[PDB]
Each structure stands twice: as C-alpha cells, then as structure tokens.
Amino acid sequence: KNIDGYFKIYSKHTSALEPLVDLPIGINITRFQTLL
Amino acid sequence: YGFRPTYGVGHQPYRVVVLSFELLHAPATVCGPKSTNLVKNKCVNFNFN
C-alpha cells in the first residue's frame, strides 16, 4: 500500500495481516513486476 | 597558500562549515530536541507523542 506519503507492507506466515515496514519513500510507482 | 605557524592573526588557516536547509514536498524525518519524569495517582496533564 502506498498513499501519497508512505509505502506500507503487510505480511503473515502460517487470519489478519500485521504491518511490517513504513518506509516514507515518496515515489510514483505505477507498474508491478517480480523476479524469480 | 603555504600556511606556517609563524604568520600573524589574519594569515592563519580557518575551517568554515556551512549548513544549508531544504524543505520540499516530502516527509520531514530530521527534527531537533525535553523529557520529564512520570507521576501517578494524581490529576495532572500529560503529553504522549
């Protein structure tokens, strides 16, 4: 999640998800891509 | 220049440091410094962040 002031990341390993990081990096992320 | 310890008062090396401030559309993670003790069982005023 990223709303105009932060980049939030939620995770949970086996239910609800807890916040993990709150980077204040403000950028204009538009696309998503992962690497194997 | 060739500085020597036998010069006068105006011909000596001086180290000058300049600090510039910047404020743009970005979160401010650099602030300045003030914490007191804790009291209980009394009607007082508190401030927790």
Image (cartoon, coloured by chain):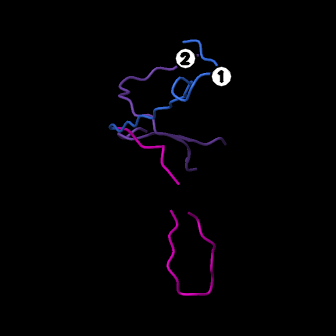
Residue at 58% over, 87% down: B42
In the rendered image of this protein, which colour is used for chain B? Answer: blue
Task: In the displayed orientation, state which residue is furthest to the left.
Answer: B25
Horizontal placement of A9 versus B41: left or right?
A: left
Residue at 40% over, 34% down: A26
Q: Which mark is residue A14?
A: none
Q: Position of residue A7 (x, y in %)?
A: 45, 37
Q: Which mark is residue B5?
A: 1
Mark 2 Cα within 10 Å, few/some/many (few <14, many 20+)?
few
Relative to B38, say whether B20 is above or below: above
Q: Please, what is the three-letter code of the amino acid marked with disc 1?
A: Pro
Residue stretch in magenta: B26-49
In the rendered image of this protein, which colour is used for chain A? Answer: purple
User: Circle 2 marks a residue in which chain?
Assistant: A
Count how many numbered circles sit on residues in the image: 2
Local SS, label 2: loop
Q: Label 2, on which residue?
A: A35
- The reply to whether callout 1 and callout 2 are in contact (CB within 8 Å) is no
Q: Position of residue A2 (x, y in %)?
A: 40, 38
Quadrant of residue B39 within the rendered picture: bottom right
Relative to A1, say whether B49 is above or below: below
